[PDB]
Image 1 (cartoon, rainbow, N blue to C red):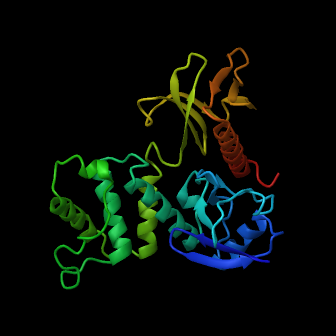
Image 2 (cartoon, rainbow, N blue to C red):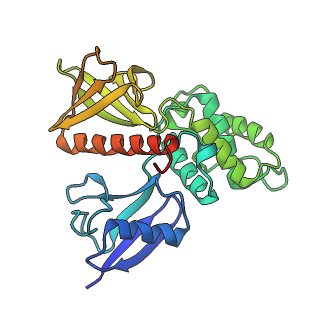
Image 3 (spheres, helix red, strand yellow):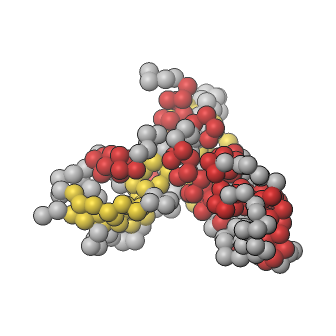
Length: 297
């Protein structure tokens, strides 16, 4: 018999059934269509497996041989897996823009992406403009932002100001966005976010030969090694151009610099589930990177 399935996006829930022989690629294409998004390369379908780990559905396989968590409606989350190099050039459909806007903003708030106080209020202003529209003394009564998650905790737990002092600071900016179309605001937000050091990078905790704890970062432009204490500034950088190739064997992964004379860089991932996760993301970003430069060739 059929299989129930629930798939959510940053703002749209989709429930429907599907035959036991359907593939992820089919499921993905299903959602893609029901929502109307064309720029698909950035997205993927995420699901918790039986043992609780968050996993990306392999499109090249039966959504039933993936060991997703067994529940009445199988649960999936449609999210952006990769990030453009520039949301201006790359994000065209107002739907893709809104989807990316919600994901990133959610990441800012959950302190998943570090963000300074000033920049965070500015980001918040664009968020209210996109939500509430233009400021209106008559409609937007003093405290209209009473129940809105605007700044990431760190910011608030940096007790310089009080709750109401932040709201004002935000309202101050809100007023300076008159006539800003709801779509423009979200794009403004992203133009700012996309420039945060932590923006769009995936971190994996790893170690070198000397058992020193480090941070591996993977993003649009390549890989970065971070000191375990600071995930904002890299300790070593490895742009795509800078690399010869990257070999994965077990929990170990090696970056071979193209500098010929240069030495190999060996790192170890804590678990296998992790090393595989990296390779996937490395390939993915590298692929989109190349597809931006050397067209459908």
